[PDB]
């Protein structure tokens, strides 16, 4: 399925080239501009654990998830991955725990040492 495919066929987008964050572009977005540090970014997403369980979805809430890029308001994989996206792009990200919740995990659903799968759509980005 999609998690296996990004694991086996994804591109390493980390600066360290340690394969901690792998990406596949599923829908090409608009133009050539990606957001910059500090921009307010609006995304839709769904996350799955490696046991197949969905652990989160903005779609199911009927509102986007909004954060300021590059400020550690989200897991490292998201700051790195969303920074590579164009407006309107949909991607898959496969996130090793060192770029996610590490040994701590995150209650109630994310265990220790969890590799996470996300589908992310970049809806919009704007400077404040
Ligand atoms: C500074 O480094 C951190 C920053 C934030 C952080 O957690 C809070 C931010 N955060 C929660 C929002 C959501 C979408 C952005 C992605 C992700 C998220 O980052 N979740 S998640 O999908 O991995 C997630 C994580 C836990 C969770 N529990 C119930 S639903 C749910 C969803 C954790 C951090 O280190 C572990």
Image (cartoon, rainbow, N blue to C red):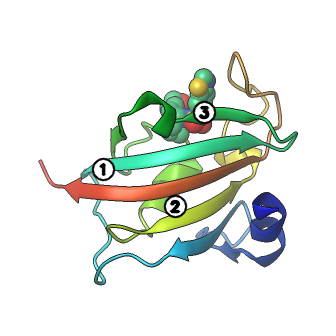
Question: Residue 102, percent across and down?
Answer: 74, 36
Question: Residue 85, percent across and down?
Answer: 42, 68
5 shown above or below 120: below
Dividing the picture into quadrants, the one containing residue 1 is bottom right
76 shown above or below 51: below
Foreground disc of the pair 2, 3: 3
- The yes-or-no answer for disc 3 within 8 Å of ligand 1 is yes
Dividing the picture into quadrants, the one containing residue 109 is top right
List the residue tagged with mark 1.
41
The residue positioned 71% from the left and 36% from the top of the image is: 54
The residue positioned 82% from the left and 29% from the top of the image is: 112
| Residue 42 located left or right of residue 92 | left
| Residue 88 located left or right of residue 121 | left
Question: Residue 58, percent across and down?
Answer: 47, 36
Question: Which label's residue is closer to the chain start, 1 or 3?
Answer: 1
- Whether residue 105 is visible to the viewer of this picture, yes or no, is yes
The residue positioned 69% from the left and 17% from the top of the image is: 107
List the residue tagged with mark 2.
81
Q: How many numbered markers are drawn?
A: 3
The residue positioned 38% from the left and 51% from the top of the image is: 70
List the residue tagged with mark 3.
56
User: In front: 127, or 52?
Assistant: 52
For the residue carrying disc 3, how many other residues have a C-alpha within 10 Å: few (<14), some (14-19), or many (20+)? Answer: some
Q: Distance between the residues labelled 1 and 3?
A: 18 Å
Which quadrant of the render holds ligand 1?
top right
């Amino acid at each position: 399925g999609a998690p296996a495919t990004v694991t086996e066929q994804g591109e390493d987008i980390t600066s360290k080239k340690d394969r901690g964050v792998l990406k596949i572009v599923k829908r090409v977005g608009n133009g050539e501009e990606t957001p910059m540090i500090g921009d307010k970014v609006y995304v839709h997403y769904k996350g799955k654990l490696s046991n197949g369980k969905k652990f989160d979805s903005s779609h199911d809430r009927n509102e986007p998830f909004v954060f300021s890029l590059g400020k550690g308001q989200v897991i490292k994989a998201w700051d790195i991955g969303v920074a590579t996206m164009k407006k309107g792009e949909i991607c898959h990200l496969l996130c090793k725990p060192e770029y996610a919740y590490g040994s701590a995990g995150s209650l109630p659903k994310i265990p220790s040492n969890a590799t996470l799968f996300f589908e992310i759509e970049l809806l919009d980005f704007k400077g404040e």
